[PDB]
């Protein structure tokens, strides 16, 4: 009894964790797992990945790749008589899915920051070609708009830590300086955190930052990142069981949602109007300046 | 035609293995070879033997074993590959099997030589889990080259590759009052954790305790501060091994052990140990951040 | 079926007209209307009359006149459009023709109000070529709003839209020993030139002589320093005019003059005039470059 | 007597100048000109542009859009019995073309910088999907390689000034700091120049920069940009005359090349070795530092 998994061939952290989670469950059920990987490139890429898994004589599919609603339906088409469970959707996808509430993760983030009293807030989305990123960005916009705040700046990365840094620097070097940032995944946050820091500012204290995923490394970012936990362990367990129900011709054939949670660590703080004095401010320097003469 | 290659890998969502598997796919794409992956439920050699049997059932044309195995365990696993070209990305002392691994002998030398050159003497080690042969070799290497530079390490400790295990060991060590000036760490995640431990212990990475990673995984260039570490080029290892495996399935290869080079990547976690006033080149940093921080408040005004 | 629209434009490779024509295409693409362009050999009204006759020969379904014409000249050109809906992107005082232009009344107010608010009193004007009615209106505007703020400009001068004419006038002015604290400039290219003139005259843009553009063309966000200027949204003007023209060819439109808004875009060329009491936020610039420059040499060490 | 021109619908400076140049000539000859524009999107886009111009009952075509060698031949196919002259090519295109020597423009740039003594050099290409940018990048690589230098970093923009800035910042913020930059067009240079400047460095003195096009604005960049002049006035004049020959069934049916030239302004300088003294270096500061106390 064998299950096929298709996944972005792109070595990001969450997709890695998700695939671990899936294996972990299947182990407990004694179902074997095989993985094919999807060469970026959208929907035709995925249609091919599927065809391998099918050739493998699998008993069911788990599509762990982010697809447009139109693209998903196409991919479902390929699964000729094979139960297929997608880990993308949006709201009224007429396919079998499990995804986390994005509606929650965005609310939570925004509500957390707004409660701390931040008004000058900025957004750092994933690559908007990806529907993940699109939804999360919409969510933020919605709940900010719903709290009479329009974000002071938005920007798009690609999920990488380094894209996080580059956008956050570009923004700061334009002289746009928020007191808080909503970031679309934990790797981009890390990069944004460095950008802040190297820009002579303090994470939390000066610019608060809020991640999205609570991937493993995040609890140990410096300082430990406040972020939206999506429980991938859970998503694995869930989807496998769901898929097995599906192959028995008896399931909640349709969309399904999983909860998220805020994880408050040390990157979020009431915005400090950290108003230092004119004459002692120039002092920090009037020593600094001398130190070089020593050199 | 086409041709299909099986990959067995730790089912453990670490960064390097993830990158390695990406690197393998990336190449096979260029050659039009398809790839399938089975995953290995920790648990050593029997686990792997099983992983293999699936890949074989899959009607593959060759195997790439991306899981860390003892010399004895590897040979066993090789046994399972009934008639199927198999290329291991582990090896050790006496391996009579087809392998490609990075020079550990280099990566350890480089690290040690880098730190010793900066003038560190009170050095500490942070190994991977020694049940893993990766970690064992790298630890031996360090020991060797330190010993070879008349230094015996002031403390060694073992993690499990995780960032969090990095933190816990580094805290445990510091809270014992053992305080090195430098740390050799066995992978970039454990480094991250060690870095936090240092930092939260009221100390400065580089300036007070220098740290040196191992892997140069993607995130590392953006650790705060950017981590100095031993680059292993996984992009390369992928490309290499696939090509090697395809040679192998054509009955004409360097049937045996093979080694890939590594390199040091000097970033901002390494610094001459506390010399009492500061270095020229990091000062124009340390200050330009100090000068940058006050630039902000003065802006804010 | 489809439908085809003719565009007449200055054959003179300036930035805004280029952008405008891009904007027009961009929209027509979305509507599936095709576009053809004829170009107007400077030379005023006869030139344009000819341009039109080609577009008509082309069997178009409507015209967009993107060339600057006197009220008298426009009416003449309108005459040529024998039975063909024609929409002008010029207008002036009494235009009884179909037009869309930006509020010049706003763009001049905004500029003047921005500078006056920063506290500049010694202000100078740098108009486009006054043979062009663009330039004339914008110059009048400035005069009006300055006069309305009890300031008469200390010097005015005319360019030709080119960057280089910007430079030559601004040098000529400075070398006469007229030195304003601020300049209103009639388009972003001339500003660039003026900015160089200032700079090479040993003075600092913003800090010493503030400068304010007009258009916010693409390049301007990257002038050194990024130019403060009046944004006219050409993307918009394109979209607007095409839709308006298509309404027109259906015999149902706001047959007459129409106005589009403008906006100020505050970048780093505008600053309270010299006080050796410099501003908090631009100081942590002026200095963090001064501090950045020395950071370099100190690094270089 | 009427000539059709197809051009990128993308409001860059050189294409604008080129189209001016074409008109300017045709005026002198009393030939009229009409322009259709090409909606990015490669070869199908262009095949359509052509069909309009043809519908217009023109007497000849000038294709001012950058095409692959394969794509060009396709587009030539569409010109059913109509003389067509392309302003793209590469070396052995079997079509009628006029382009500038890219082989020269790259040599000149490299030779200019190498002569000044720069070794740590960096490249800033146009969008490599465009064949323009590809050739120019190859050229640089070639002549650098030919001068025993491998570039310290290469990067790709999109012709925009802003993409010039973003790549140059990204590079500098990575801590890669060349002494010289070869840039693939004058707008990207401008952006790179700001990036340098805002990075606390001096154009020329610290990082020399060399453009490509000598478009109008460039003589007034701050500081006036050193760049490879391509004479678009000339290219206009040339191509119109050539096209008219062509419609008379008597021309140099084939590839043709135009020269380029270096224009030395104030962005190029022997790389500085200025070791300033320890004790006076710290002094620049120990005043600077006080100035802020004023506030």
Image (cartoon, coloured by chain):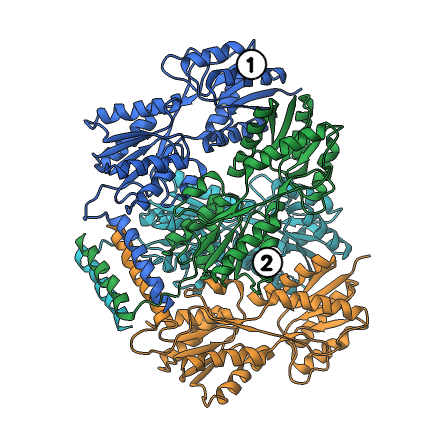
Chain colours: A cyan, B orange, C blue, D green
Percent coordinates x, y for residue D283 in the rendering: 24, 65
The local secondary structure at tag 2 comes to helix
At which x and y percent is residue C220? 41, 39
Q: Is residue B54 rendered to the left or right of residue B141?
A: right
Disc sitting over residue D143 in the figure? 2
Residue at (76, 57) in percent of width and height? A56
Asked whether residue A182 is in view, the answer is no
Figure check: A181 above or below C83:
below
Quarter of the figure that contains the N terminus of chain D: top right
The answer to which of D219 and C259 lies nearer the viewer is D219
Percent position (x, y) of residue D138?
61, 54
Q: Residues within 10 Å of mark 2 (few under 14, many from 20)?
A: many
Q: Which residue is disc 1 drawn over?
A: C249
Q: Nearer the viewer, residue B258 or A206?
A: B258
Q: Is residue A48 above or below residue B230?
A: above
Quarter of image, res B74:
bottom right
Q: CA distance from mark 2 to mark 1?
A: 57 Å
Chain identifier of the residue bearing label 2 in the image: D
């Amino acid at each position: 009894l064998l299950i096929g998994v298709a996944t972005s061939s792109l070595a990001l952290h969450a997709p890695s964790q998700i695939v671990a989670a899936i294996k972990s469950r299947a182990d407990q059920l004694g179902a074997s797992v095989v993985v094919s990987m999807v060469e970026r490139s959208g929907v035709e890429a995925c249609k091919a990945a599927v065809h391998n898994l099918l050739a493998q004589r699998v008993s069911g599919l788990i599509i762990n790749y982010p697809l447009d609603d139109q693209d998903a339906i196409a991919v479902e088409a390929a699964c000729t008589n094979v139960p297929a469970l997608f880990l993308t959707a949006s709201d009224q996808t007429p396919l079998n899915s499990i995804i986390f509430s994005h509606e929650d993760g965005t609310r939570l983030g925004v509500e957390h920051l707004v409660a701390l009293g931040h008004q000058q807030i900025a957004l750092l989305a994933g690559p908007l070609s990806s529907v993940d990123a699109r939804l999360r960005l919409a969510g933020w916009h919605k709940y900010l708009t719903r709290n009479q705040i329009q974000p002071i700046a938005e920007r798009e990365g690609d999920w990488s830590a380094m894209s996080g840094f580059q956008q956050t620097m570009q923004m700061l070097n334009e002289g746009i300086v928020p007191t808080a940032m909503l970031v679309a995944n934990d790797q981009m946050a890390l990069g944004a955190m460095r950008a802040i820091t190297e820009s002579g500012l303090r994470v939390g204290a000066d610019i608060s930052v809020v991640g999205y995923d609570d991937t493993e490394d995040s609890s140990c970012y410096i300082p430990p990142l406040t972020t939206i936990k999506q429980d991938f362990r859970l998503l694995g367990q869930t989807s496998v069981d769901r898929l097995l129900q599906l192959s028995q011709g008896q399931a909640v054939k349709g969309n399904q949602l999983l909860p998220v949670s805020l994880v408050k660590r040390k990157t979020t703080l009431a915005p400090n109007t950290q108003t230092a004095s004119p004459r002692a401010l120039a002092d920090s320097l009037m020593q600094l300046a001398r130190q070089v003469s020593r050199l």
